Amino acid sequence: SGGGMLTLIQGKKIVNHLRSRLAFEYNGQLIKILSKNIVAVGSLRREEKMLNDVDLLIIVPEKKLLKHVLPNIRIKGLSFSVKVCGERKCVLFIEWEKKTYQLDLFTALAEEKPYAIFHFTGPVSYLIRIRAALKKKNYKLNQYGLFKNQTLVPLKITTEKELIKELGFTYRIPKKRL
Amino acid sequence: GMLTLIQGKKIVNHLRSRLAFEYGQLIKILSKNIVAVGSLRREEKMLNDVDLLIIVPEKKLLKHVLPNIRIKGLSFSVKVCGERKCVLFIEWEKKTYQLDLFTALAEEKPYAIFHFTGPVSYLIRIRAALKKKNYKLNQYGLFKNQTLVPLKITTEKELIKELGFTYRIPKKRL
DNA sequence: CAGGATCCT
DNA sequence: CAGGATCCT
Ligand SMILES: Nc1nc2c(ncn2[C@H]2C[C@H](O)[C@@H](COP(=O)(O)OP(=O)(O)OP(=O)(O)O)O2)c(=O)[nH]1
Ligand SMILES: Nc1nc2c(ncn2[C@H]2C[C@H](O)[C@@H](COP(=O)(O)OP(=O)(O)OP(=O)(O)O)O2)c(=O)[nH]1
Ligand SMILES: [Mn+2]
Ligand SMILES: [Mn+2]
């Protein structure tokens, strides 16, 4: 909200800096968050020229760690403060090159990954259309899975691309989703 | 600000004839559709606020009742306001007090009254007991496997006894 | 469309 | 225990 606007390139340099610097405390132990479990989402992934904030999705190996990842987040040698922080969303105000920016951290479990990536990539208008179409065929789609009568629909997929095509829609790269 | 029980009762009495909503038309809220709930109904000597449940004749009016609430002969402001809860800061005498307005549909009335009467500790026990027999109780109804359990009850007393619990007057619930 | 964190009810 | 309003995501 109050955070400064970033250029796409500014955002990419922040993500790159953070890729090696995130960690969390787990019952005392300090566990590094692997760069490969950090997916850049939001307008940055859609490669928009200006961004209101930086959105990172964190992929967590086991459900037991959800309690601990965002609520005990750490960033090596970066000045920041917490706006709000639960298990699924944490909003930080970070200091970067003498400016204050909003950094949004989200968590997905490994089995949720492609649904999460699809959700947090957006844009909002695109997701409303996609979900409404699935709603007319009696499905509910969210960031956790595809559902039918409050029951998980177990799709045999791994990637976002595979998800979208399994949902019965045309795949477009993030940049071309409107 | 904190109220005595009697202060609270005089506020409710004043408001009983003064609530209305728009909606183009201005519709009076009947005193008989206004139930005092919360610690006032439990007759606690001191209260943190005044809680009133408003009973709505039809579901189509939910959109309009609290979101277009009006009070004749009173100065106030809205804190927050949705279809189910509206919180007002009212001027009474020479003081500011919190007034909480809740809505229940007619078919929900006894569930709402039971919920908003409390106290919280009592409701947690009651609901946990029903949870062990696979029911869910809330302010809207009694449910089983995401299906409304159609008890044909009218009053709160009838509800509690139908739920299989001992009826106690609000003052003695704990 | 769908859901999350906060601070309540 | 179970859920609501606000302002986000
Ligand atoms: N389903 C759904 N998802 C949303 C909604 N708002 C945001 N999201 C998801 C998709 C977004 O790409 C992601 C990040 O939200 P942001 O508000 O940061 O928007 P985005 O990053 O797209 O642009 P911006 O930060 O404004 O440059 O969260 C919503 O109303 N519904
Ligand atoms: N199920 C449930 N009901 C609640 C909860 N908190 C409040 N309520 C309901 C029952 C309460 O009697 C009613 C009014 O809440 P209040 O916070 O105003 O407490 P109460 O009025 O009993 O005392 P006070 O207002 O503090 O004098 O709302 C809760 O956590 N769970
Ligand atoms: Mn963003
Ligand atoms: Mn109260």
Image (cartoon, coloured by chain):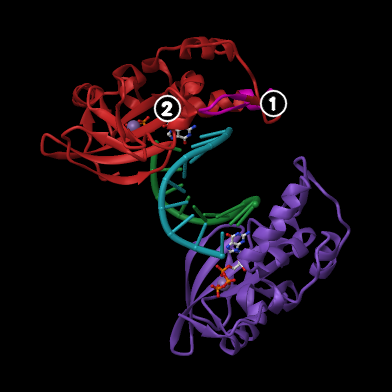
Chain colours: A red, B purple, C cyan, D green
On screen, residue C1 versus residue B55, left or right, reads left
Residue A87 quadrant: top left
Q: Quadrant of the N terminus of chain A?
A: top left
- Residue placed under numbered mark 1 in the picture: A138
Residue A123 visible (yes or no): no
Q: Which circle marks residue A120 in the picture?
A: 2
Give residue B148's position: percent from left, percent from top: 80, 47
Q: Quadrant of residue A39?
A: top left
Q: Secondary structure at mark 2?
A: helix
For residue A156, above or below residue B140: above
Front position in the image: B53 or A131: B53
Residue A114 lies, in percent from the top left, at 48, 18
Residue at 76% across, 59% down: B108
**Residue at 52% in and 14% down:** A164
Kindly tell me whether mark 2's CB lies below 8 Å from ligand 1: yes
Along the viewing direction, whichever of A136 and A143 lies nearer the viewer: A143
Is A138 magenta? The answer is yes
Q: The residue marked by circle 2 belongs to what chain? A: A
Q: Nearer the viewer, residue A125 or A42?
A: A42
The CA span between labels 2 and 1 is: 23 Å
* Magenta-highlighted residues: A134-146
